[PDB]
Protein backbone atom coordinates (compact mmCIF):
# COMPACT_ATOMS: atom_id res chain seq x y z
CA UNK A 1 0.00 0.00 0.00
CA UNK A 2 1.52 3.29 -1.22
CA UNK A 3 2.23 5.73 1.65
CA UNK A 4 0.15 8.57 0.23
CA UNK A 5 -2.86 6.21 0.27
CA UNK A 6 -2.20 4.98 3.77
CA UNK A 7 -1.22 8.14 5.67
CA UNK A 8 -4.20 10.20 6.77
CA UNK A 9 -4.52 13.64 5.17
CA UNK A 10 -3.91 15.38 8.52
CA UNK A 11 -0.48 13.73 8.74
CA UNK A 12 0.33 14.51 5.12
CA UNK A 13 -0.65 18.11 5.87
CA UNK A 14 2.63 18.69 7.71
CA UNK A 15 4.56 17.75 4.53
CA UNK A 16 5.31 19.48 1.20
CA UNK A 17 4.82 17.76 -2.17
CA UNK A 18 8.48 16.77 -2.56
CA UNK A 19 8.48 15.22 0.91
CA UNK A 20 5.44 13.17 -0.14
CA UNK A 21 7.28 12.14 -3.32
CA UNK A 22 10.27 11.08 -1.22
CA UNK A 23 7.99 8.88 0.92
CA UNK A 24 6.64 7.16 -2.15
CA UNK A 25 10.07 6.71 -3.70
CA UNK A 26 11.57 5.31 -0.48
CA UNK A 27 8.65 2.89 -0.16
CA UNK A 28 9.07 1.70 -3.75
CA UNK A 29 12.79 1.15 -3.21
CA UNK A 30 13.19 -0.23 0.32
CA UNK A 31 10.03 -2.30 0.66
CA UNK A 32 9.52 -0.97 4.18
CA UNK A 33 5.84 -0.61 4.99
CA UNK A 34 4.31 2.88 5.00
CA UNK A 35 4.81 3.34 8.75
CA UNK A 36 8.50 2.50 8.75
CA UNK A 37 9.09 4.34 5.47
CA UNK A 38 7.68 7.41 7.15
CA UNK A 39 9.92 6.87 10.15
CA UNK A 40 13.05 6.47 8.01
CA UNK A 41 12.22 9.60 6.07
CA UNK A 42 11.78 11.46 9.35
CA UNK A 43 15.01 10.03 10.80
CA UNK A 44 16.88 11.06 7.63
CA UNK A 45 15.60 14.62 7.97
CA UNK A 46 13.83 14.14 4.59
CA UNK A 47 16.99 13.54 2.58
CA UNK A 48 16.99 10.66 0.14
CA UNK A 49 20.72 9.95 0.11
CA UNK A 50 20.86 10.06 3.92
CA UNK A 51 17.83 7.77 4.17
CA UNK A 52 19.29 5.17 1.80
CA UNK A 53 22.71 5.27 3.46
CA UNK A 54 21.10 5.07 6.88
CA UNK A 55 18.96 2.14 5.79
CA UNK A 56 21.91 0.32 4.21
CA UNK A 57 24.00 0.79 7.37
CA UNK A 58 21.28 -0.02 9.93
CA UNK A 59 19.59 -3.06 8.36
CA UNK A 60 20.22 -5.25 11.37
CA UNK A 61 18.26 -2.83 13.53
CA UNK A 62 15.00 -3.14 11.63
CA UNK A 63 12.40 -5.66 12.87
CA UNK A 64 10.65 -8.00 10.50
CA UNK A 65 7.37 -6.24 11.30
CA UNK A 66 8.64 -3.17 9.40
CA UNK A 67 8.37 -5.04 6.11
CA UNK A 68 4.91 -6.49 6.66
CA UNK A 69 2.11 -4.91 4.64
Image: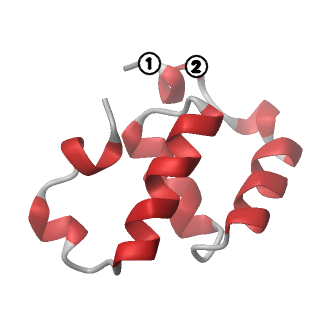
19 relative to 1 in the view: left or right: right
Q: Quadrant of the C terminus?
A: top left
Question: Residue 44 occupies which quadrant of the picture?
Answer: bottom right
| Residue located at (45% from left, 72% from top) | 19
Front residue (pair 68, 24): 24
In what element is the residue under mark 1? Answer: loop
12 is higher (above) or lower (below) than 6: below
3 is higher (above) or lower (below) than 49: above
Question: Residue 29 occupies which quadrant of the picture?
Answer: top right
Percent position of residue 50, x then y: 77, 66
Question: Residue 15 occupies which quadrant of the picture?
Answer: bottom left
57 relative to 17 in the view: left or right: right
| Residue located at (84% from left, 55% from top) | 53
| Residue located at (60% from left, 27% from top) | 63
- Classed neighbour count for the residue bearing mark 2: other residues with Cα under 10 Å, few (<14), some (14–19), many (≥20): few
In what element is the residue under mark 2? Answer: helix
Count how many numbered circles sit on residues in the image: 2
Residue at far right of view: 57
- For label 2, the residue is 64
* Nearer the camera: disc 2 or disc 1: 1
Percent position of residue 40, x then y: 58, 55
In three-dimensional space, the C-alpha distance between marks 2 and 1, rounded to whole angstroms, equals 7 Å
Percent position of residue 51, x then y: 70, 59
Asked whether the residues under the numbered discs 2 and 1 touch, taking CB atoms below 8 Å apart as contact, a structural biologist would say yes
| Residue located at (78% from left, 64% from top) | 49
**Residue 68 circle label:** 1
Amino acid sequence: MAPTLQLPPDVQSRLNPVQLELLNKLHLETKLNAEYTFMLAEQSNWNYEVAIKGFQSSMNGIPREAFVQ
